[PDB]
Image (cartoon, coloured by chain):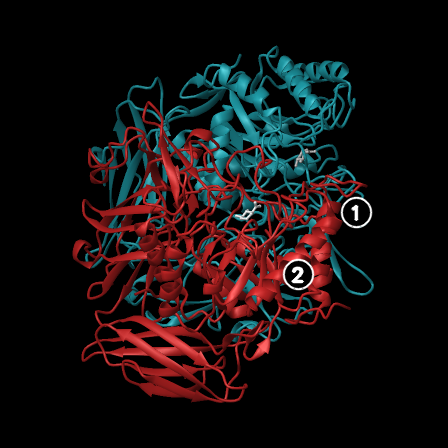
Chain colours: A cyan, B red
Amino acid sequence: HMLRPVETPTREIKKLDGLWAFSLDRENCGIDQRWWESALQESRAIAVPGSFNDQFADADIRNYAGNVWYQREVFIPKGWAGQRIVLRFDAVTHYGKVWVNNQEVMEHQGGYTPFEADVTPYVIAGKSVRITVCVNNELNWQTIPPGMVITDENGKKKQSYFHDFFNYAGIHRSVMLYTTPNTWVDDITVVTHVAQDCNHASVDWQVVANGDVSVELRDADQQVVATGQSGTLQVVNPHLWQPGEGYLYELCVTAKSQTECDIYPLRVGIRSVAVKGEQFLINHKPFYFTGFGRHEDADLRGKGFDNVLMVHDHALMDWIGANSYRTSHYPYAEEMLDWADEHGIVVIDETAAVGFNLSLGIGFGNKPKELYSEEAVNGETQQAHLQAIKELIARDKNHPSVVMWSIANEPDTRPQGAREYFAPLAEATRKLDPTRPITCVNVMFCDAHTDTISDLFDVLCLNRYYGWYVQSGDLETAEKVLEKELLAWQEKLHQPIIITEYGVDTLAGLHSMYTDMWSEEYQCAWLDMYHRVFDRVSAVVGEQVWNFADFATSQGILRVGGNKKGIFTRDRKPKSAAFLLQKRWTGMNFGEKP
Amino acid sequence: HMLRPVETPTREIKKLDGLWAFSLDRENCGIDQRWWESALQESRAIAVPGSFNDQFADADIRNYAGNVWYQREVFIPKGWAGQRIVLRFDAVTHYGKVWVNNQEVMEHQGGYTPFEADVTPYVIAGKSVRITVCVNNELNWQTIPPGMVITDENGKKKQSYFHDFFNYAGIHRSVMLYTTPNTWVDDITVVTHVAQDCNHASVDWQVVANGDVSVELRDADQQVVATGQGTSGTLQVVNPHLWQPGEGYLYELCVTAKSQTECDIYPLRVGIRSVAVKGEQFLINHKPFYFTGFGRHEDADLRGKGFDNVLMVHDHALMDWIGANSYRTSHYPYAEEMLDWADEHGIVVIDETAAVGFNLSLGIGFEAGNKPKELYSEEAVNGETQQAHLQAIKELIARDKNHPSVVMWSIANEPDTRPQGAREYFAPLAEATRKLDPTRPITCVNVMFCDAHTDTISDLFDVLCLNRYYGWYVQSGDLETAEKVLEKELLAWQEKLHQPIIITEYGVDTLAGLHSMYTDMWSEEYQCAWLDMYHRVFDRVSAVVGEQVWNFADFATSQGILRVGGNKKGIFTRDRKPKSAAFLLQKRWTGMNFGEKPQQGG
Ligand SMILES: O=C(O)[C@H]1CNC[C@@H](O)[C@@H]1O
Ligand SMILES: O=C(O)[C@H]1CNC[C@@H](O)[C@@H]1O
């Protein structure tokens, strides 16, 4: 059960003061000596939220593998006596264990979604409370994403993994205490059915075993459009949420007990999404995706959320004419999807299940020789995977801006076990939520004649790098390979085709008369050639450029101080292909394919 | 009366949530049609804290001159019934006017120090209250810093100013509502006297509004070491753990404000430390100290001068790594988080007002008009510029009075002191500052072309602060001639004043990546040679007790043929990557013993 806390007759004290106390645990004796009982000795100030890696300009902290300890004091507001008090972490990347003054509150494996707990019997209103959080950043074969910790014969752990971005960790998002009465709306699901945009229904389902519920549908002018009294349904008149506007009704659910009362406001976007034939229909009209795969990657904070960075990246995506993006390779911060709700941005929401593939040269030992096996990606990783889809859906269900779930990124689907693995996951997800199409984004070398699993999904998502990783430098042959491959998919599946990734590394400042790789002239010619090919194949309904910005990776001979396929630098300065994308994307009609 | 909000039987609701509503006012009718009365129209989301300029990647918001509108709703807690509620803005840059549901509560001009208002009579506990703020970013001759707003024929205003950083504006630090009981400690002043490091007296004086006071002084182990009574006139005798550069041991002063019915307790951090200028030495706890480090800026990539916690932790990691022990709040007061950090980690800090650009002889700044023909006149820098300047000195001292890390007040930065009337202006504010805070030495930072033969006002101050660029702006490229000019100038300054000499700005513009076998201007090799030549001169002049490299990091300036996308004299880049010179400084500042002048050897 998860909703984003709001303020009303429910309160919140945001505890991301910044400046917790922080210390490594190189000897792995924190839990044994129970460091949560006292103040951490030999600690230093750390900023919350933000990754602990890049915060101290220290190579030993940055590449650290083990447990790290956060700690902070905080006075509980005296006006909270007799309320339910919830300690919420919006994200603790990979693993957290929480103590409130010698008492353990909660522990969570899965570093991108919230976890909260009821802390009433362990705090008294008005006195100071100590919170210790033991964060762990290790990946093994049953974490999402997977990884492999290797120890030397001397005892220092080095982490290996199989995805392209760097393995930042720490407290990445909001820690907050929020209160609620002891009669409290705990969960609301709303499904919205449309059919020629003139009168449509909002089925309701909501759970609070603590009180009886009234529901009342407000509009943007705070005037009531419908009312009902769990398992509700309301019928309404026309003004849909559309990728242009993003008109949001606001549905206040009241939970009445005789003694107490609780009001929770949930914003509803009224619209439909459905795949038919080769079309991706938003409110029964075909839609053409444009935009980026992104990353939560910033200069000094790592993957730490930041409001200024959010406003400025959306100013850039607005200027460049993108209507859509994909939360590439892990669930994003919540405010991202709240912003897309208000501004009508289409989002592909995606689980952290990346790196199920031992055949890439990206992302940092001796790896197992068959991927699907006990040794790696066994039954326990399948259920850990499924738990990640449950948590992601449970968090983002009501968001209108999420038009599609992506259960995994670039899995190796050639060995079997790939289908024996992904078939139950696609079916569990489809029943967890049937209001949105389902996809799995497919890696390049699993071409149309080789991949095993994409007929279990609704939309086909392709990451193609012809002219980069294969046919390197030759736009002409890469053109012909590209335009032979997507026609091959179209005949095979007759599904909508989104190219969720296409991009080439580009050094900001490298200019060439010869249009060769790494130069800005090549990123321009490359993107345009992919565009010529997209426009001639009817089945492609979306383009998303690989990354919007340069981002940090693990060290390697293939990554010049990071992944450089950005349209913008890590500084968010535009490479000269930003004006290529702005000109094409804003010249087209909104949401419609050239 | 100014105090840092703390949480001890007192509560705060940080309204920094960012994502306020934001709107410009190009027709300048927001005051006319009463924009605070309803929700801002055609607004957009803005992050707070943070300058508004670089946030939307649009030049016409960036160079906007006029009023900006922020707006936000906030639910006010039920359990603050019998409590006093205060709305506080730790910085609204330049001018800010606030409305609490159609009622103006506050108004402030001064972009870098906090202002607050008591909001109890217009707030209902439990109901949502809407907060509208009108911010202005204009500078005239009686603002600090000064400037000239230039109207074209169509009413579009362009701001010209005379300082070398961009004029970022908006709500730059943290906006909060906090409580207090209706009996409350409103101001504390603490002075600490040192007598050869064995026993000392902490003069206390407190202005509680509404109660008798006891004080209690606790150590780092929270054990009581001294008690006292009375609204003031508390002086406590210790056998102490001094606040030292390097460690920064902080006692704790618990001030009790007890009335008949209510109670209020405020914990103020107290560093036991004495600062004194004796001879050509700057003594901290009666020992000669050598400053190393930086002039800084509150400047980052997309938040402008917006405060940020990751950025503060990382920059202190770097300043600790490179061996710096000091810095100067270059050109405006910094956030209090910065000076609280310096208090904890024993970092020596020169505090500075915003009085920069009292000089119309520099190519620095924005030149979008015609500058006045005389700086010290009724048209520019008049008696009201002097009162605004005094006001800025009082607010600055009123906030940082008890920070042990502050060792000096900087009244102004590089004023032009050749014209008569520079002393008619600066003498009264120098004595008024000494009457505001007589426990810390006083300085004014001296511009390069006011040499020892020409400067008129430096004898009014305790420490001589120099900004020199020989071999850059003059004798360009010529290291061997520059060495002679610099050593001649520094020996002249010492002989004329016999004050301590801190070089608060020396640096050269340096493109990261530009390398040269000829050690040319703008190359990383030049930066290195230039810094090291300056260092050989310093080490030969006894009166020099400090070196502060001009900037820690590259920062944004206004457009001009002298500023390649900003000022590039940083040791680090804007995204905090080290230039070659960073390893030069690290070898010097970590090779010296801590806090002591290199004896011309190694
Ligand atoms: O090679 C690339 O740049 C991309 C290929 N597909 C997956 C991405 O994580 C990766 O970054
Ligand atoms: O020109 C420079 O680089 C510096 C000269 N002295 C004043 C500073 O504000 C300025 O940044």
Frontmost residue, A163 versus B570: B570
Picture coordinates of residue A81, whole percent (x, y): 29, 67
Name the element at disc 2: helix
Quadrant in which the N terminus of chain B is drawn: bottom left
Q: Chain of mark 1?
A: A
Kindly identify the residue that appears in the image at 23 percent across and 64 percent down.
B84
Picture coordinates of residue B193, whole percent (x, y): 45, 82
CB of residue at label 1: within 8 Å of ligand 1? no
Disc sitting over residue B321 in the figure: 2
CB of residue at label 2: within 8 Å of ligand 2? no
Q: Chain of mark 2?
A: B
**Which circle, 2 or 1, is nearer the viewer?**
2
Give the labeled residue for mark 1. Answer: A367
Q: In the rendered image of this protein, does residue A591 appear above or below residue B363?
A: above
Picture coordinates of residue B556, whole percent (x, y): 53, 41
User: Would residue B481 be found to the left or right of residue A334 on screen?
Assistant: right
Picture coordinates of residue B359, whole percent (x, y): 46, 46
User: Would residue A124 be found to the left or right of residue B536 on screen?
Assistant: left
Q: Is residue A120 visible?
A: no
Disc sitting over residue A421 in the figure: none
Q: Amino acid at mark 1?
A: Lys
Name the element at disc 1: loop
Frontmost residue, B216 versus B375: B375
Q: Residue furthest top?
A: A536
Q: Is residue A426 visible?
A: yes
Kindly identify the residue that appears in the image at 36 percent across and 23 percent down.
A194
Q: Residue furthest left?
A: B121
Neighbours of disc 1 within 10 Å: few (<14), some (14-19), many (20+): few
Q: Amino acid at mark 2?
A: Trp
Measured in 3D between alpha carbons, the distance from the residue under mark 2 to the one under mark 1, in whole angstroms, is 38 Å
Quadrant in which the C terminus of chain B is drawn: bottom right
